[PDB]
Image 1 (cartoon, rainbow over the protein chains, first blue to last red):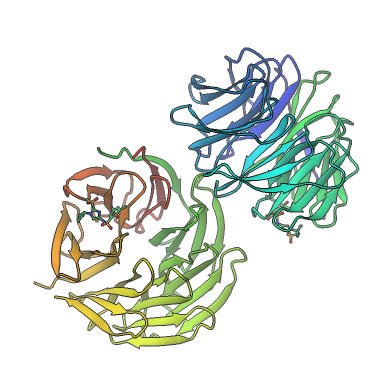
Image 2 (image 1 turned 45 degrees about the vertical axis):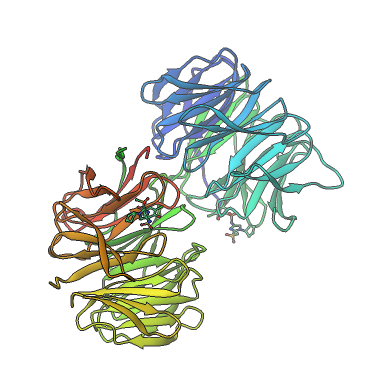
Length: 304
Length: 302
Ligand SMILES: CS(=O)(=O)c1nc(NS(=O)(=O)c2cc(Br)cc(Cl)c2O)cn1C1CCCC1
Ligand SMILES: CS(=O)(=O)c1nc(NS(=O)(=O)c2cc(Br)cc(Cl)c2O)cn1C1CCCC1
């Protein structure tokens, strides 16, 4: 069994490299962010452009949705995050405190907190309602590439170019676990697995690894794509077959069998690095986005 | 201070009346049961359907979570209770012994015991590990409408259409107290601090009792409850509220101390038979009978 993702729509509009794509939790929308300082909202099923959201003063590296799909948070090189009302496009709050580019962000499942990571090497936890910074974690000794909450919000995982992944207790701010090897290439992405027991980490040795972080054991590796430079998102695809999905610096989307690690599909069409992919929450749909020779988002659909 | 619960999601999927909704202790999930013989699991923050759990041969009246959120127990008209692994959906044990419909169930905080009540007028205490019945208590003289453990599991409270609430010692099975006009008692549970019980009677009244002193400290009224066993709850995450469904299709919310109705949630199109309060967020789940068949999730700032 292999998926058969086929191209359905190409979405143009951004005027610099795209940086992130995310489907809303209710399945209805895709949000994209770009170095052009904009967020764009698109229909998830037909690619229809819905709106542009503007106000950051420099490029945007990441965007994340609240669980009720009503809010977005964005992380910008202007050293802020912004919380947006998706329906109106209005900026509700500007989150100030990082001292350099904000690279990654996420809401907790409860969506009362936002976590952010920055080039300033810190991880910050923010109150959604007030916009205030609740905690600053001295998390890493180099830029922070990803931050993600687990399924009950009680943990955060962070990754950094310092080579580490760390697990944090949300409520206390304490580091519960550091994952480190004899060799520690930059970690360019991390997230919790669907069941919360694993983390999937990308390193710039062209490799994805699935770790049991409690036991400190690497269960699976996914290779054959190209990733030595950019922070490229990876995903778990849960709607049909159990796949790992990632972009790649050879302009393809790679899809692997979770268990066997075999590459099961490569999606061809983009004309630059595929910096970001997202998997739809209920349908077998992938969104992919590329850097500045391309500047487009593609929507792909599969039977499994 | 008054809450401002607003509708966030409507969860459709059951094909007959919903009978109970419960949040998992870790806050991640809502479990629902229905007369359609199914349990459904839903995401607590995005309302997304997760899975259906099936195997009972007749409708289900109640479902309850273990304290690690890994197991469910369900009580059915098929006269059995089933213990389920939530991750796999598999039935681990079928608890056999009641001679009629099983109406209510709960784990203790340690989650090594389950308590059940039945139309057979008994309360049973079951070993989770083996599924064996440990004790049968001749608890009531009419159907048992609710059973609940206190904060550490040392006590059980039961209620019945016979008009009584009874407090039982878990370890010994002995009745420590009987609270005795005697309208049918359609629901009971211990308060968060274990010192009170909140009891619903089919005279449209919720009462908060100090059961050790035999004193009724508060009543909550203004809703409609003369027929169904409607759950009620203590809301501990924001303001101190009592929450209940109602036979006029609304969710009622009262101030614990003043007994004032502070909000009524409108949206359901049938009796709101069950409500649940999320363990850490100000989120209510409500569920309704068969003209409606949906669960609604509501969110408040306090
Ligand atoms: C193969 S397996 O199906 O047995 C399995 N499930 C998990 N859990 S996971 O990574 O969180 C997860 C990933 C996806 Br993609 C989808 C879902 Cl639903 C999901 O739960 C891991 N594995 C195996 C690989 C490593 C241990 C055995
Ligand atoms: C008003 S009060 O705050 O003084 C108060 N607390 C309790 N304890 S309770 O019922 O277990 C309880 C209920 C809720 Br709802 C939430 C929490 Cl957290 C909680 O602990 C009772 N009362 C008063 C009602 C009658 C006696 C005085």
